Image (cartoon, rainbow, N blue to C red; front, side):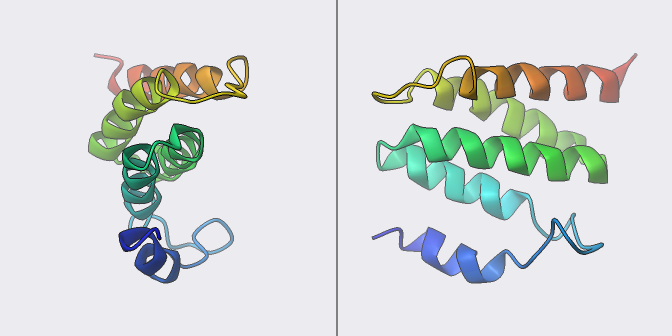
Length: 104
């Protein structure tokens, strides 16, 4: 069970209480992909959001754009107990962060 994720649970160190960010985020993003591949796109969407927060702070436009894109499409793939007004709004967050990162 989890396989790649199980490794990434040890590869992703405490980023959200330490000044290490750019080294991670993308690890939660990769875990998120795997969750959606196993059908459980709820945890997928959560990890794409928490990843997008890390990318946003590190101003990693590639990963933030990549997380935003995958976020909204993992949400449409979320099974029963589909949170909707919690999980889907996270995609809208990642939209706002991404567009403000551009401001071209």
